[PDB]
Image (tube, rainbow, N blue to C red; front, side, top):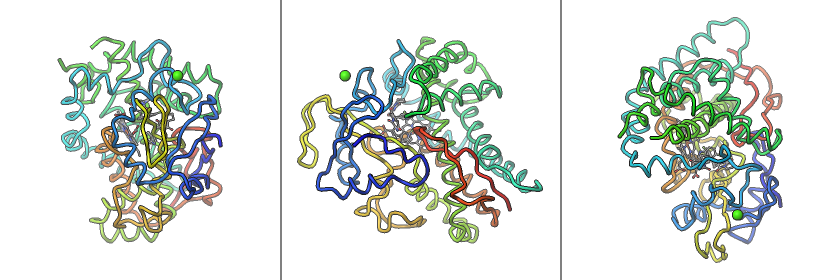
Length: 390
Ligand code: HEM
Ligand SMILES: O=C1N[C@@H](Cc2c[nH]c3ccc(F)cc23)C(=O)N2CCC[C@@H]12
Ligand SMILES: O=C1N[C@@H](Cc2c[nH]c3ccc(F)cc23)C(=O)N2CCC[C@@H]12
Ligand SMILES: [Ca+2]
């Protein structure tokens, strides 16, 4: 069985449920991209055990030379590629909390909600249809990255970074050397500009890092991290969440009537809406055992968050979008020590988007869901456009 399963749209591959129901708690696959053997976990209970055992190491699975699911290493050649580790290493946990935590949300939620309303209001004033991907998600996610993470970017700089992320974070669709060069271009951009970006107005995280008590190569790796972790993820997820909402007008109607139910809908979108077409992954740093299956030192085990989020043993009717369902914690931000530190800002922008939609009932797709076209091969699913109208 080769990996990934080429399920580039919101329709999850049937392989995930087939492995979930199989008689083994971990299943062998082979990387289509490298030929590397890998282990794959699809059950919630097993995923909790793996992701909360620190002897399964994320950094070891990211290291140059690890068995891997990507066709190329996710780093500019000659660089370390372990930015968030390096930053927590140098003693910046405090600064990451300031730039990503509840205080950052308090600083930014005002303009984020103003911008979501402004973008939706301009679309509502247009005669004709519009594109929720290009006209709502792209400006909102670009503003999030610029104001809270990198600093003010020109349009051309934003486009270059967006292109680098779409070219480098891929299972297929580009040559290996094009994929590698995307990381080289991004790194060389931040070698030239990361310090410049820190010296602009704002409280964006890259400034906070650059002002804390770092070499240009380290600051450049911080910039590349914020692009790959913050830009295609937020844009892919907001696009997918809008598709989910547009396909559930009864749910939107309930949020319109009961705005206090929006936070529950945000959490259910994170469970229900698929994002990555690959898996979180960890290297066994010694011989380990998971639900009876031996994992030798150096072997890499992946967890599909999509598969876990749709596990019927965890969630009753897992394929139903049900805000306010009462089951366990979703896996949309992961689990354990590597739980997405962007979760506060992500939840902020997701909530701003849900509220903007819930205030304007009647918003609908201008084509059929099957006429939606998907970028093929991205790590993080994204439709090419979302034609919509009132
Ligand atoms: C402001 C935007 C975001 C920022 C700055 C951000 C930042 C990060 C960083 C730095 C990590 C690495 C943590 C580590 O390896 O210890 C991470 C992990 C993660 N992020 Fe985000 N993120 C953002 C948005 C998102 C979104 C929108 C999603 C999902 C919808 C998401 C899902 C995840 C997941 C699942 C992980 C865990 C990966 C793993 O366990 O290996 N992130 N994020
Ligand atoms: O910091 C990291 N953590 C893990 C998981 C992760 C978080 N965000 C991501 C965005 C793209 C991607 F391919 C992987 C990740 C990982 O694999 N990393 C390589 C690139 C960023 C790095
Ligand atoms: O496809 C991928 N997924 C991440 C882990 C992950 C799963 N779901 C996510 C949602 C958001 C995010 F930022 C990261 C992930 C990861 O390690 N990769 C290495 C190569 C493919 C990439
Ligand atoms: Ca190796």
